[PDB]
Image: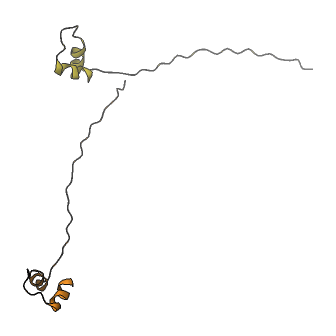
Chain colours: A yellow, B orange
Amino acid sequence: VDQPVHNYMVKRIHKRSLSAAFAIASEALSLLSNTYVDGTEIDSSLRIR
Amino acid sequence: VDQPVHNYMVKRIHKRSLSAAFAIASEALSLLSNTYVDGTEIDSSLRIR
């Protein structure tokens, strides 16, 4: 004669990641880090670029 | 890690031509350049032709 059976199962978290890169030339860093020293006509177009 | 790329290309004009010809008989030249000399009834039909 048979009797009912119960089950108990446990799983776990596996961890992953995603990495994406992004670069800037040092020319643009010098172009943005002025702090109110520059502002001539030819530099504004380069900053906008 | 991968970084996004940009592509710059330049394409160039190639130049060609088309040629067609058109001829005049010498009799038609000497007959179309009377400049009020003959005024006859027979050469008027040749001028129209």
In the picture, measured across the screen, residue A7 lies left or right of residue B30, that is right
- Judged from this view, the residue extending furthest toward the right is A1
Residue B15 lies in quadrant = bottom left
In depth, the one of A45 and A6 nearer the eye is A45
In the picture, measured across the screen, residue A38 lies left or right of residue B9, that is left
Residue in the picture at 52% in, 16% down? A15
In the image, residue B14 sits, relative to residue A19, either above or below, namely: below
Residue in the picture at 88% in, 17% down? A3
Which quarter of the rendered picture does the C terminus of chain B lie within? bottom left
Q: Position of residue A41 (x, y in %)?
A: 17, 20
In depth, the one of B4 and B29 nearer the eye is B29
Which quarter of the rendered picture does the N terminus of chain B lie within? top left
In the picture, measured across the screen, residue B10 lies left or right of residue B40, that is right
In the image, residue B30 sits, relative to residue A31, either above or below, namely: below
Residue B3 lies in quadrant = top left
Residue in the picture at 34% in, 21% down? A22
In depth, the one of B43 and A6 nearer the eye is B43
Q: Position of residue B5 (x, y in %)?
A: 32, 31
